[PDB]
Length: 257
Image (cartoon, rainbow, N blue to C red):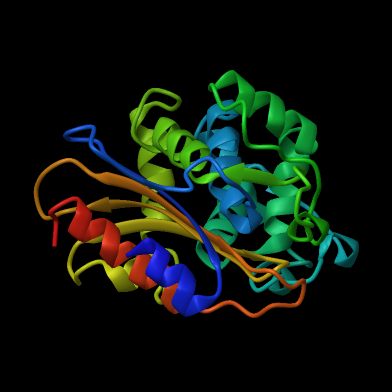
């Protein structure tokens, strides 16, 4: 079924899913690298949370037009007032605000700092190097700003569900991701209505289209999923339907739907 989706959508798919209740997995090219694009924003907030108290998220960040980049849906409205770190995390996660990601990344010490903190949580794969807009531009074979489906799942799980954060911080992260506005055509579109989904989307050059998520069936332990994709041509379009359909194959394979 994954090969058939690659054929229908002229794309390369990377899939990893873990049922945290059983330890069963679904995998298809799970260790192939893709540009992570804005899926990195979830791990970036994980690191922010780890390094701050919750009250410390109330720090107000002043910024200017020079901090705004290519896509600033929330941050462009608040240049005059600033935004708190909490507000920047909300913007980054729920709207994929690129300026918010760059401001958070600067607060935590820049891409190299983020990389060091990911290594500390056990991720030796994810390779943050650049800010937006450049991080979304990755050529075939390059490893800058890439990860794999397996590593993104492992890292997302570690922050949201395991012991890289204390419970109140896990809850912030999960609630922001559950209320994401950008993912309705992706993993959410392959999950029955009513099941809670926390997700973060991304897109990059070479038609890269990604979504990472935690899916809660009405009872029982959650599934952590990464669906990554890319194409042959630099300026290629993506199709969200590939990601929705891949998700439905994962849900069948896990006997959840």
